[PDB]
Image (cartoon, grey):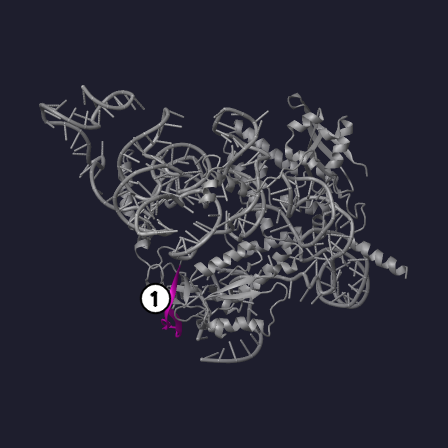
Amino acid sequence: PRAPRTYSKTYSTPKRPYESSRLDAELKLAGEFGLKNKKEIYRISFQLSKIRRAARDLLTRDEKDPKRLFEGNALIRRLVRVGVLSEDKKKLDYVLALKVEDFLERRLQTQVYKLGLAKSVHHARVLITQRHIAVGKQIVNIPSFMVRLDSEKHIDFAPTSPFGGARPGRVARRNAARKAEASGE
Amino acid sequence: GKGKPRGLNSARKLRVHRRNNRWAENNYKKRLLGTAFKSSPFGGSSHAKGIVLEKLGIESKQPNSAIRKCVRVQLIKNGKKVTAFVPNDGCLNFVDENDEVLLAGFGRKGKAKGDIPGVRFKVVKVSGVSLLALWKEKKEKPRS
Amino acid sequence: DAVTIRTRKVISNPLLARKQFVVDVLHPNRANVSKDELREKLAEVYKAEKDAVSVFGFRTQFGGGKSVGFGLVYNSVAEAKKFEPTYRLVRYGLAEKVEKASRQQRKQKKNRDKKIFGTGKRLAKKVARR
Amino acid sequence: LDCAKVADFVVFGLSGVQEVDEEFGEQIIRALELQGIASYIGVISNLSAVHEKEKFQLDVKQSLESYFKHFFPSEERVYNLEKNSDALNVLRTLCQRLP
RNA sequence: GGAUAGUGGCCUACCAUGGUUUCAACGGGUAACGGGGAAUAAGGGUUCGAUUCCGGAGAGGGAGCCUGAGAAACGGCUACCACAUCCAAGGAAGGCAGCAGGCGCGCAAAUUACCCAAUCCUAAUUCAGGGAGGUAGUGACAAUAAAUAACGAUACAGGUUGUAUUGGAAUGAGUACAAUGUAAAUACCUUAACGAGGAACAAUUGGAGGGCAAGUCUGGUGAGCAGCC
């Protein structure tokens, strides 16, 4: 038979369910950034967990070990590109100081709010899912899309929508027609 | 010290000693002897199906007082005879003799549950319909 | 709006008397472009007969506006007719669909014939006499 | 009731065009269950009467199965006799299976 | 010495009395095919591997053998053992642990569908053949992304935030002309027309003494609840 397709699980569940102090901290993030699930938080903390595991491992290696040089530089370079880590803090020891809010701040859903365009993080989510936002030429409709530092110049309304320059939507057209027809009465 | 050999070539004695002492662990002994195949009503399966022989009431152990409702069942694969609890009170109206039922463990890994002396299994389905669906009036039992 | 056609990664392939390339199409404000229209515009730009042009395998970008596919142009109508798969020629109407029986029926006929030795003009006569 | 009381198999006919009436049609099903039934089969015979595309037939068939399963949760299939494969399947069951 | 493609107690004649073991031989058990591997992340370990790749074995059970470079072959043959089919009662024929399907079993598992277009293999061969293989159907095993509403006005209260009458905008679920897709089709991606105000286009499953988030509420009662207390 054909070779197996590989797949993997992307989140982890907190090991004590009813730790009351934790429940409060999670709900503030969801209200601040307009998330729909706790899973959206678990996903981020799962990624952050693995980054620390790798970084902490490398720090056992001596400086000028060729592996620490090669892979350590890759990891730092890759986080700077998305803007999670400042290019001032461009050193491996600072990777251990990142926290969840550093990643949520970079989601397309929040960037479309900080730029204007929308007027709440709840309004921003609606526009993305309804296909009004484009990055460069490509229409994007996923809220969790991580905006790389180059792309921020190119976020704007899509060419093929109202707000972007196309024809009015289905409901505006219906209203104009009935009123025009009645105005002929 | 510590009453166990430490020497660098002593490996044979250490491992042999460990084997002899694992037989005191209770669940370990069950696997190696294969006890769940040779005995216990389910042959190591999580469920079994059986036929209802008669209807019973079982009074609670102290301090409580209540005649709790149970049935005798005979398992189809083993022919062994067992007593099972029926949840949700008035659901006892849905079970009658020569019904076929699906049984599950009563949650305590072969021990009886709570007040009830010697009752280890609970009914899950009757005649192919679930008791929970009957209790909530979601389905209907065809007679036989 | 005007359609724009572009070709990329152009290879000349003397071993099969053809040119082969990527076809890239921009088409704002319409759903897509038909293969039949692409075949015409490619024919006049490469100065070929329309029957020597073959085009397949398109998909259109998410959010629309662009499509990408693959294209061939043969050095003659005769050479196209020998190297091209028959199913593509049917799409272009350069060949006629053959009318064989269903796959299960053909197999069952074969197994009946295996039971006859020789041509079977005899035996038929013997059965007629019975 | 007297006829169905003696059967090994009861074949329930359903219509794709008109749904069963609560004042009569359902009372048949309800009464037969409470006297007891040796076995039961769900059948459709006229689903092509609402053809536009057979996906529209599938939409109806799913509704009938969900309805039928309410009374007979042991069964999850209703056959369409307009299709040779289903009708042969039904015939085989009556011949081969025990009640 | 014989036999084998060939070494060798592999077998035969004659001769000697040896070989293994508490560093566990021999015997018994395995709900035991071996390995690459899988789950569980402080470290050391514990449990599992019938199953996509590599190697072994078998074609109901034992034995024998023809053809051939290669078989102790089972979609080859012969006999016995156990099953079992047709008949004019003289005889003849058999092997799904290939694909699809049926009975039985049980807690426990899909269509008697389309095709050689792709991957490759075989033949005297570019061309024929391939249930190997691919396509679609069934499919809450497991996995990825992610709808069920957003924003103004008015009235009221608060310091730009809550609580109720009212107005334009936005969109896919769904349906459908067309093109694209494909061996031919279905679906996805794209798109003319249609498609929301209780936006009935209506989200469930378990809990509220403690472990362990959340009721001195309110009506009934004096069989029920509870893994544990």
- Viewport quadrant of the C terminus of chain B: bottom left
Of E127 and C121, nearer the camera is C121
Find residue E119 and report its image quarter: top right
Find residue B61 and report its image quarter: bottom left
Residue count near mark 1 (Cα–Cα under 10 Å), binned few <14, some 14–19, many ≥20: some
In magenta, the rendered stretch is: B48-74
Q: Position of residue A137 (x, y in %)?
A: 74, 39
Farthest residue in the right direction? Answer: A184
Using residue D13 as the reference point, say whether residue E164 is left or right of it: right
Using residue A103 as the reference point, say whether residue E160 is left or right of it: right
Q: Is residue B30 visible?
A: no
Residue at position x 28%, y 47% in the image: B21
Most common SS among magenta residues = strand
Q: Position of residue A139 (x, y in %)?
A: 72, 43
Of B4 and B108, nearer the camera is B108
Residue at position x 36%, y 55% in the image: B44
Residue named by callout 1: B118
Q: Is residue A104 visible?
A: yes
Using residue B9 as the reference point, say whether residue E160 is left or right of it: right
State the SS at label 1. loop
Q: Position of residue B63 (x, y in %)?
A: 37, 72
- Viewport quadrant of the N terminus of chain B: top left
Q: Chain of mark 1?
A: B
Q: Is residue A146 magenta?
A: no
Residue at position x 45%, y 41% in the image: C126
Q: Position of residue E196 (x, y in %)?
A: 74, 60
Residue at position x 61%, y 60% in the image: D47
Total numbered badges shown on the rendered structure: 1
Q: Is residue B49 magenta?
A: yes
In the image, residue C45 sits, relative to residue B100, either above or below, namely above
Inspect the image, locate mark 1, and give the three-letter code of the amino acid beneath it: Gly
